[PDB]
């Protein structure tokens, strides 16, 4: 029974710039012409 | 008083957890949500009227 130094004590990931894009949901809007005649 | 001293204190300074005010993140605005439809009911009803 002899004491001894058996206690040995010993003691940022990826920084960066980020840009986040979402999935576009707006419906595509274009111009439509409708020709027609009215007979009354 | 130059004989010096002994700093036997084992430092255990644990920084407090900083406060965080969570944002109310909004991905799509209400305008995009209303514009994300092939058919709009208000337009159809207005044209019928």
Image (cartoon, helix red, strand yellow):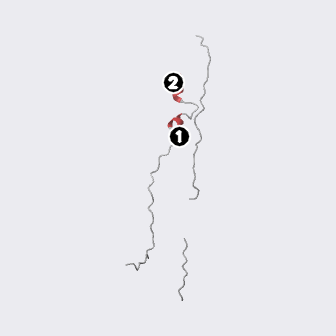
The alpha-carbon separation of the residues under discs 1 and 2 comes to: 26 Å
Q: Is residue A14 above or below residue B23?
A: below
The residue sitting at the top extreme is A40
> What residue do we see at 53% from left, 27% from top?
B43
Q: Nearer the viewer, mark 1 or mark 2?
A: 1
Asked whether disc 1 touches disc 2, contact meaning CB atoms under 8 Å apart, the reply is no
Location of mark 1 (residue): B28
Q: Residue at x 53, y 34 (%)?
A: B34
As drawn, B5 above or below A20: below
Q: Nearer the viewer, residue B4 or A6?
A: B4
Q: Which residue occupies the foreground of this view, A18 or A23?
A: A18
In the picture as drawn, the residue positioned furthest to the bottom comes out as A1
| Residue that numbered label 2 is attached to | B46
Residue closer to the observer: A17 or B29: A17
Q: Position of residue A11 (x, y in %)?
A: 54, 70
Element type where label 2 sits in the image: helix
Please provide percent x and percent y for residue A15.
Answer: 57, 55
Q: Could you say whether the residue bearing mark 1 is in a helix, strand or loop?
A: loop
Most extreme residue toward the front is B2
- The answer to whether residue B37 is left or right of residue B22 is right
Could you confirm whether marks 1 and 2 are on the same chain? yes
Counting other residues with Cα less than 10 Å from the Cα at mark 2, is it few (<14), some (14-19), or many (20 or more)? few
x 60%, y 27%: residue: A30
């Amino acid at each position: 029974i002899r004491f001894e130094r058996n206690i040995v004590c010993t003691s940022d990931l990826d920084e960066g710039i980020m840009v986040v894009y979402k999935r576009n949901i707006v419906a595509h809007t274009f111009k439509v012409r409708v020709y027609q005649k009215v007979l009354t | 008083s130059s004989i010096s001293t002994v700093d036997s204190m084992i430092a255990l300074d644990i920084d407090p957890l900083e406060n965080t005010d969570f944002r109310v993140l909004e991905l799509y605005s209400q305008k995009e949500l209303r514009s994300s439809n092939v058919f709009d009911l208000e337009e159809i009803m207005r044209e019928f009227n």
